[PDB]
Image (cartoon, rainbow, N blue to C red):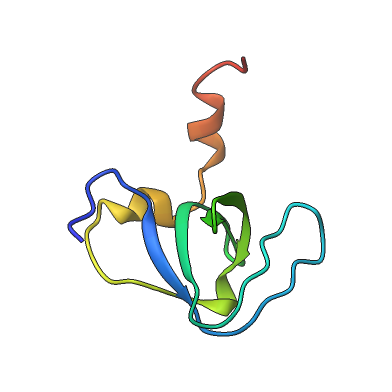
Length: 86
């Protein structure tokens, strides 16, 4: 960064094969884009034009901004319930 509002970059450090239809598959060295931390183990992100889930333990997130703290932390309950559903 500074990244402002843009998605965070990460690189795959290990190969990963997706085990469900929601999960991205990628090879070590791949460039990944991260939109939002879903949980300690998982991100919502993008690889090769396709949005899906990416496991935290298979990647290295690139440095800096904060900023990134919002996208890097899972959304809290109180944040989600602050607005009605669509």
